Amino acid sequence: IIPFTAQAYEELSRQFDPQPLAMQFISQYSPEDIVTAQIEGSSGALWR
Amino acid sequence: NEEADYLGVRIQLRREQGFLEWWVIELQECRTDCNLLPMVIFSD
Amino acid sequence: ISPPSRAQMKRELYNGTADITLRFTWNFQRDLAKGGTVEYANEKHMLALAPNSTARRQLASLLEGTSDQSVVIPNLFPKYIRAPNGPEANPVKQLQPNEEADYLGVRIQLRREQGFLEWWVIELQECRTDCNLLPMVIFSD
Image 1 (cartoon, rainbow over the protein chains, first blue to last red):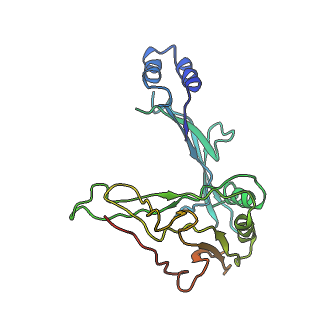
Image 2 (cartoon, rainbow over the protein chains, first blue to last red):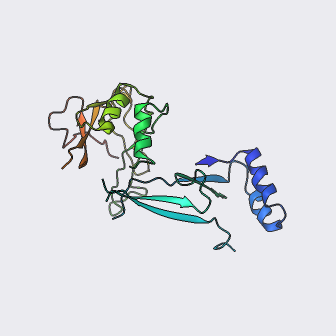
Image 3 (tube, one colour):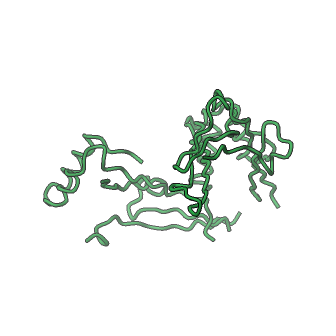
């Protein structure tokens, strides 16, 4: 999990800047707020 | 769409009998997201 | 774990220069009938696994194929824990002065007895009956 930095936050906000409310969500949430969901995908845990 | 604008996800059961049923969560465009899917959580 | 994860986990212990997060979470779920807001008192006692250390080289061979490697985890089993009704399994300091080096010498043994039948016994550096029943203590509040 990566706590998004100020620069990272700017990136996300700019990605969704065209949509006002999309950018709003990101921008309103404080920097080091938006966290990165780097969920693991590899397995080994068998299907049961 | 938030159901059609999330992120294209794929699944791959890896039953390599040696069934050794594993389960990798890939992406429709898996680059390194078969082992590390990078989404985001706008936290509050 | 699997070829995209266990073979990678293997590799880490084999070579891969990384520090496996050995979070020894000591969750202590109590009750709520006698009180205990966040009864579950938990603390992830992490042991960053130094790339190919003595412990990780034992783990290399453990995950290679053999099941006879006593992985030395430097004193990391809290034998005295001042846990309260909050969510923290903080061990008593002074009870265990180093409290990371004064916990209790813990060992690990993967028992892959192909018949890989990968089991996992938590032994002790001085395992008498603590390979099946590790006796620590929780100073409860």
